[PDB]
Amino acid sequence: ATCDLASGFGVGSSLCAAHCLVKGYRGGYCKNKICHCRDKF
Image (cartoon, rainbow, N blue to C red; front, top):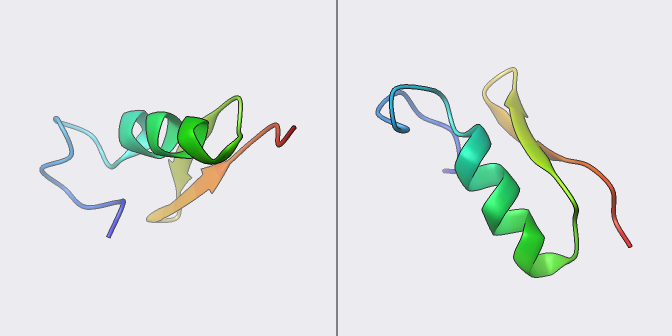
């Protein structure tokens, strides 16, 4: 899962962002324990 607890003292926003950058997003943030990406080109 993208989001957890030991996500670098967070939830999983940094991973979500970087991970989605690979796909084609310009941002990523974990909300409601779910990786929600933003800006899909």
